[PDB]
Amino acid sequence: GAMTCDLPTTYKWNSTGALAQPKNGWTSLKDFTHVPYNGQHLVYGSMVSGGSYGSMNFGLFTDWNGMGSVSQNKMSQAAVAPTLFYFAPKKVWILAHQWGPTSFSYRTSSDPTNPNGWSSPQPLFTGTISGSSTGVIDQTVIGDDTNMYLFFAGDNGKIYRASMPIGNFPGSFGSSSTVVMSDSTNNLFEAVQVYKLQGQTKYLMIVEAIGSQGRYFRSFTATSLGGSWTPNAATESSPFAGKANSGATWTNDISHGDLIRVTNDQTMTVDPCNLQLLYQGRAPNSGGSYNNLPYRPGLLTLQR
Ligand SMILES: [Ca+2]
């Protein structure tokens, strides 16, 4: 301004009240750092959520009485319910997931061994579904020579599909989808996975189902990713994998995971000459709220 001023030797201040309350179920906002940003206020800080420290920024605001109105944005890199593959046509690693900004997300990387090397999340899908407690969940992605495909579930007995030309990937599938199969909620519940069979033009779909004895997978096949699916092993007594045939005594559930793929690429090829399933399992008498179930990895190896 017009002149330089010195610090006083003795300080007196006026104060605002609290300028913002923590949003998002957080306990506190802390440790503020501020810069002027194009005539506006840009503030980062620490926060506490459920006892643990994280960080955040406030949306831009012009006047101090607006600080309490703007967004409070967690610094986050979560990729819940992921799908990992190398997209060979553009030599880029892909991590698809849910609970990002849009219905499904993807991130890119040049080295998937680094868990903090992923891009910020890009839109993979933006659509919604009706008749579902959860909304769209548990995406998986697979390509053939012509198209990339997105499949997903809804805890509602339906499996859904969208497609794009392969040259357009990576990118968003948009909002539209097509119902692929429908059954009771328990029979087509979640954790859809789709694979190509090594050496033949045939595809395998597995879907997690709710059984009387625990979670299990039902299998289907197709000769075209865009076609109809025929049941393979699809009852609880004769499942693709479940308590009836897993040989696993540490868990009843055989639940959301991935067949061991013989390639890292977008074709999701598996080799049924040694079919193996990396599943989540839990102690049989574990219980309580779904979020706290004590799931751990297990591996099934087909008895030939
Ligand atoms: Ca039903």
Image (cartoon, grey):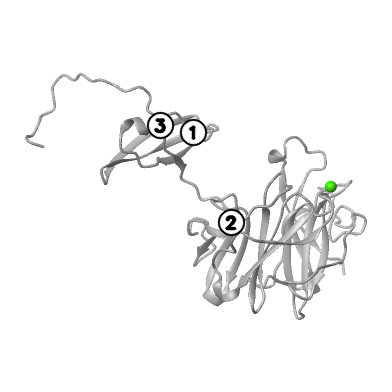
Label drawn at residue 226: none
Q: CA distance from mark 1 to mark 2?
A: 25 Å
Amino acid type at mark 1: Lys
Q: Quadrant of the N terminus?
A: top left
Of tags 1 and 2, which is closer to the observer? 2
Name above or below for residue 100 compared with residue 275: above
Q: Which residue is mark 1?
A: 23
Image quarter of residue 219: bottom right
Q: Residues within 10 Å of mark 3 (few under 14, many from 20)?
A: some
Q: Are the residues flagged by discs 2 and 3 in contact, CB closer than 8 Å?
A: no
Q: Which residue is mark 2?
A: 126
Name above or below for residue 174 compared with residue 23: below
Q: Nearer the viewer, residue 201 or 47?
A: 201
Q: Earlier in the sequence, mark 2 or mark 3?
A: 3
Q: Quadrant of the C terminus?
A: bottom right
Q: Residues within 10 Å of mark 1 (few under 14, many from 20)?
A: some
Task: From the top left corner, tell me how far across and down residue 120 is, in percent.
Answer: 48, 56
Q: Which residue is mark 3?
A: 68
Q: Earlier in the sequence, mark 1 or mark 3?
A: 1
Kindly tell me whether mark 3's CB lies below 8 Å from ligand 1: no
Q: Residue at x 78, y 52 (%)?
A: 189
Q: Nearer the viewer, residue 225 or 265?
A: 225
Q: Residue at x 67, y 48 (%)?
A: 135
Task: From the top left corner, tell me how far across and down residue 112 is, in percent.
Answer: 54, 63
Q: Earlier in the sequence, mark 1 or mark 2?
A: 1
Image quarter of residue 300: bottom right
Amino acid type at mark 3: Gly
Q: SS at mark 1?
A: loop
